Image (cartoon, rainbow, N blue to C red; front, side, top):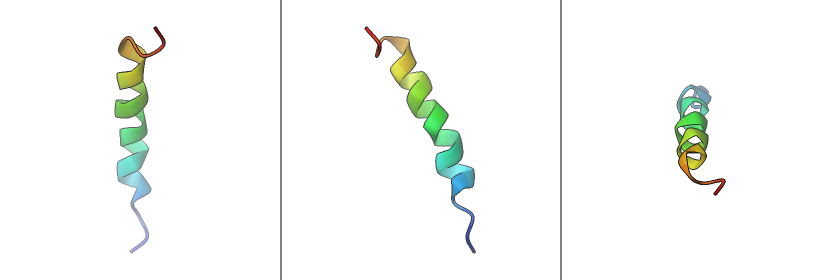
Length: 25
């Protein structure tokens, strides 16, 4: 079973999108 990206793959967004709020600032 080699399928984890399916997770961290969707998390990367939840992370970036999180740093998009006021992260840049």
